[PDB]
Amino acid sequence: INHNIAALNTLNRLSSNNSASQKNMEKLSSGLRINRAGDDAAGLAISEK
Amino acid sequence: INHNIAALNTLNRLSSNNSASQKNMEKLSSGLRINRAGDDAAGLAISEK
Amino acid sequence: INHNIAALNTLNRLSSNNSASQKNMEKLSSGLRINRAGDDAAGLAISEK
Amino acid sequence: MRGQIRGLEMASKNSQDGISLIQTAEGALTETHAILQRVRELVVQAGNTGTQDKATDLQSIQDGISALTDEIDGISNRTEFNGKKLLDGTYKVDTATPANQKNLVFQIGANATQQISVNIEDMGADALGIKEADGSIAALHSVNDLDVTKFADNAADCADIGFDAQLKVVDEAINQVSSQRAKLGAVQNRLEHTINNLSASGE
Amino acid sequence: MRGQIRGLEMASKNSQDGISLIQTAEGALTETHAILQRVRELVVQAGNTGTQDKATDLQSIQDGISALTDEIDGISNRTEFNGKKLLDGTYKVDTATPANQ
Amino acid sequence: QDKATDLQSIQDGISALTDEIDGISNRTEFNGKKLLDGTYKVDTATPANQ
Amino acid sequence: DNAADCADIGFDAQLKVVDEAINQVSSQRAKLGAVQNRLEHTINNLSASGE
Amino acid sequence: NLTAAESRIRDVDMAKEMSEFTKNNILSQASQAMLAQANQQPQNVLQLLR
Amino acid sequence: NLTAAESRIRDVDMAKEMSEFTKNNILSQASQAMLAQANQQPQNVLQLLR
Amino acid sequence: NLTAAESRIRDVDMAKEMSEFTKNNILSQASQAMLAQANQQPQNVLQLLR
């Protein structure tokens, strides 16, 4: 089944890890634990206020 | 009996070994000794909690 | 009865074996255990879906 | 012999197909679970940070949670195998009613009756299975997410919204995922050892 | 001589058939054994990790084990030779009863 | 796991196989005598019909 | 509807039909080949006796 | 999981299929050798009964 | 302490798992070589009994 | 955000595409080996039916 094996779970981990490290940078670079996205829009809207 | 010999026990070992190395990767790639499957659902459900 | 002997059962085995090895190739070449033919149209129609 | 051999070949086929179903539902429940982790994060935040968050903040959270609900429901209503909604929480509710079960049978053995009985019962509305869905609590906190402003009224005072019941819904929802995956993986192991038998015995 | 020769040909046949039965049951018992290894893994875990596992955890384990039981029973109730359930545990229980062997 | 249509696909194959078995039993003739006429020599406990 | 539940369609009866159908072929061929052997030994007798 | 499911449907045991391929080659060749022999025997007959 | 507890549950002995990975590669490859040999022997037979 | 949007349109899963590339190489080579075998069988036939 050679043509069916790619360790696709590894590939999924890869996508996950790349986004993960990306997020780390974005927070590091910006100095923001807050998200740009509305994820925790409570805490965001607070800090906005 | 040429048509009956394929070392089918070797073939069974082959299937076993391919799944084995696969599992090794999946844990290595994910960094998870835990299973996705409920095998040791005790330890899983614990780590979930 | 010289004109009546051809080991026709051997000939029938021959036709069978040629088609057999042919099928093996076709699956090997295509990488498909599935049939082109509707033989196991259940499993086929599943994989289609 | 050949009757049984061929039956063992199709047995291996059927069991592998079993596995495919399993791992489908398995990965889906893993993602569900990951959501539920996020949910509990939002529960602890939906402690209102005590009283510090305002009603709008709880509504922002609740928008996020209802969004997550819609995703859980999406899992349970998109996870199909051959059209069979494998996370149809009403697939095999035992009910104490044999007539209504859709028993997830797996005929594997080349011999008659050699079948495996499996149970599906999880879905987005399946959270604290007290017996069934209780009401606003025990299921519909997973669906409707009671932490709107009722929480700010009684952050602890009445259990129904006093943070307690909600966290218990989430905890039990997770526990039901855990046990569902436990059954699921139990059968996974079964089919592993089955196939090993089918292989050796077939040989 | 030929009577014995032919009887030896069918003897070889019968003995090879013996072997086929043997190796059938053999491989089945090997798989059974492998399960039992997994079982003992689940026994040592079903030391509850002492007390650390909870009742639900033990039930998750027990679900797995009862599943394994069903597989062992499946071995012993699927391993047939010519219909003869070769791992019928009641096949040849000596019993101290010749009538039932 | 198979659905009703899948069982019907299988059943189409099997009924096809039936038609082939019937074809065997209704084509296997010797000198016209349908040698696999299943009603050729049904003993029946009736000597008159054998 | 009833993959096992009633034997009539519960996979059991069907597999038993197939198994017995095969067994009836087996025994039919058993009789058939018994007669084959008979005619083998018959012909050997007819040949020797004829000679 | 779904591509794996498909892969199970289309699972080629490539080792099996190469092995079976090999066997069927062998069997074809053997059978043809025997067909040659089937053509050889009646020639021996021809000479011997000339 | 809690993330450490989890880590114990999900503890990957990465060295073990790379090692075992290696082994299982070796074992797969070896077994396939033997499957080739299983296909070679009956060919030798074919020639030798031709 | 816009260059990211484009990037999603032109998103190459480079790992996927290297993997699929690999596979298609394998598959091409395998199929050609089988084409050789397709040319070998009728030669065996030629000798065997000479």
Image (cartoon, coloured by chain):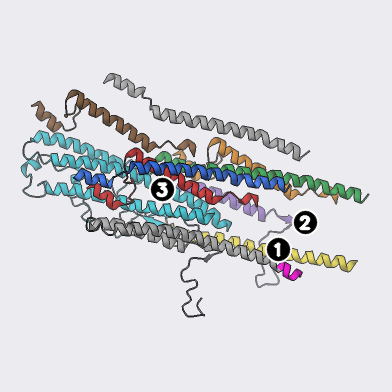
Chain colours: A brown, B red, C orange, D cyan, F purple, G yellow, H green, I blue
Which residue appears at 74% of the width and 63% of the height?
G36
The vertical placement of F13 against D149, above or below, is below
Residue G16 or residue F38, whichever sits in front: G16
Q: Dot 2 lies on which element?
A: loop
The vertical placement of A22 against C11, above or below, is above
Residue E47 or residue E66, whichever sits in front: E47
Residue C14: image quadrant is top right
Q: Which residues lie in the magenta part?
A: E1-6
Q: Which residue is mark 1?
A: G32
Whether label 2 touches label 3, CB < 8 Å: no
Residue sticking out furthest to the right: H50
How many numbered badges does the structure rendering display?
3
* Three-letter code for the amino acid on which mark 2 is drawn: Asn
Q: Is residue D103 magenta?
A: no
Q: Is residue E5 magenta?
A: yes
* Three-letter code for the amino acid on which mark 3 is drawn: Ile
Locate residue E28, reporting x and y percent. Answer: 48, 60
